[PDB]
Image (spheres, coloured by chain):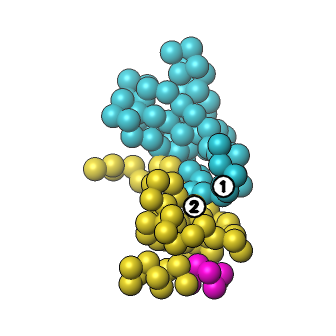
Chain colours: A yellow, B cyan
Amino acid sequence: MSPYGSDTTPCCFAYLSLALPRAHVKEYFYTSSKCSNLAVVFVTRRNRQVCANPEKKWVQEYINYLEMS
Amino acid sequence: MSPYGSDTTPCCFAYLSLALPRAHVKEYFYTSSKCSNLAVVFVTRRNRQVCANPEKKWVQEYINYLEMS
């Protein structure tokens, strides 16, 4: 437990019109609530995370695909 | 290297006047360049990081102390 919650917080704002194939992605995640902008963090099969804003339809498609698969 | 980057940025904007003693900290560090605010991340002896803006004297002293020790 950390009594002091004023620590390093993962935040991000990015997007990509050409998203990596769904076969390379493992799952999706959302940026910290501390972030002024809510973004989606895709975790690849290589466990490498990337940030993309949910307003991109590809992100929606990938989220919709990863939520069902 | 990553041809496709833009991922979670460890950022922070906080401070604490009642900071933990130098015996509780191991070292200091700076926030990522993607951060809109430069902050200092202190790494405790428990591998727990914490942030504090360098504008605080405690941070300056701890930086000056941790840079030498």
**Could you tell me which secondary element the residue under label 2 belongs to?**
strand
Q: Which mark is residue A50?
A: 2
Residue type, numbered disc 2: Val
The residue marked by circle 2 belongs to what chain?
A
Indicate yes or no whether the magenta region holds residue A59. Answer: yes
Indicate yes or no whether the magenta region holds residue A20. Answer: no
Question: Magenta region's main secondary structure?
Answer: helix
Image point (47%, 53%), residue name: A46
Horizontal placement of A22 versus A36: left or right? left
Residue type, numbered disc 1: Gly
Give the image location of residue B26, x and y in percent. 44, 26
Horizontal placement of B54 versus B58: left or right? right
The answer, for residue A4, to whether it is visible in the render is: yes
Depth check, front residue: B52 or A24: A24
Give the image location of residue A63, x and y in percent. 49, 80
Instruction: Tell if the residue under mark 2 belongs to the same chain as the one under mark 1.
Output: no
The residue marked by circle 1 belongs to what chain?
B
**Could you tell me which secondary element the residue under label 1 belongs to?**
loop
Image point (45%, 41%), residue name: B49
Image point (47%, 49%), residue name: A7
Image point (43%, 69%), residue name: A27
Q: Which residue is mark 1?
A: B5
Q: Quadrant of residue B47?
A: top left
Q: Residues within 10 Å of mark 1 (few under 14, many from 20)?
A: few
Region rendered in magenta: A56-60
Q: Residues within 10 Å of mark 2 (few under 14, many from 20)?
A: many
Label 2–label 1 contact, CB within 8 A: yes
